[PDB]
Length: 264
Ligand SMILES: *C/C=C(C)/C=C/C=C(C)/C=C/C1=C(C)CCCC1(C)C
Ligand SMILES: CCCCCCCC/C=C/CCCCCCCC(=O)O
Ligand SMILES: CCCCCCCC/C=C\CCCCCCCC(=O)O
Ligand SMILES: [Cl-]
Ligand SMILES: [Cl-]
Image (cartoon, rainbow, N blue to C red):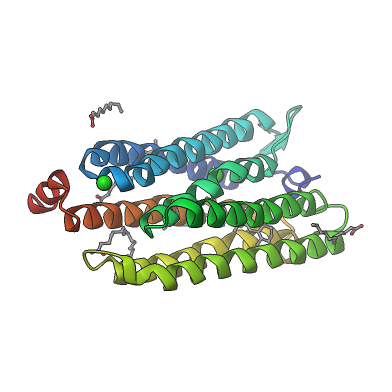
């Protein structure tokens, strides 16, 4: 059902995809240890935002590791190229994982925005429903990336509608609650918005690769885009979320945060 299955791969193509996925694992588990260790410097009100980065790191790291082993299981070097064996490789599993990781990314943002109570629960609920709409409709569309490109486009448009509405919820909350934020993080949080707009848009671009580059180099491009997108949307984003948490914590008087920021 997926374009990866259509092609044989050069050793270069195959080894590059393997290295991209493997590097992805390493970056996410490296960042995991950073988040774990810095969490002690985060005030209770925010500490779950840092814990969510740990959860996203393992989740994304495990999907990348899964993809990497599936890639090596699926292909063997036969008659001068890597050819499909009995097991299959697919990006479908990333979609399933987004059902968990996207809500985690959105919740960590709501936490540092100082939302709480009813507003937090209601905002999270609408964001998660929009996210799930996006992800499910996209998952369905990509089943057609070989057999019916028109269907892939239409499901893609539906998904993009959910995306745009989600992004409008996010920006609305960010630009409304920016003024509650401490320690100068009212400025930092605007950069977080733009980082999300940029990084998250890489996913629909990857989605469309079967429409504009249906060949083995397109397969490579798609994995490359997911790699850039994962690192930006999870790791760089989590690092900014954690900086914001620690800075707000120190401004609120949490002494471990003040001491951590002091000794750097
Ligand atoms: C860490 C993983 C992240 C942030 C994943 C984000 C995924 C998206 C923003 C996906 C969006 C899509 C569209 C807007 C249209 C095409 C189908 C999807 C699901 C790829
Ligand atoms: C936020 C940035 C994240 C960067 C992650 C990506 C790093 C890897 C960069 C690779 C550059 C391209 C290498 C050349 C491709 C060879 C093509 C081939 O034969 O398949
Ligand atoms: C197994 C694959 C290769 C091993 C990867 C190990 C190298 C890790 C490099 C970067 C990971 C990013 C983690 C960011 C932590 C904070 C960075 C910082 O404080 O500047
Ligand atoms: Cl607190
Ligand atoms: Cl993920």
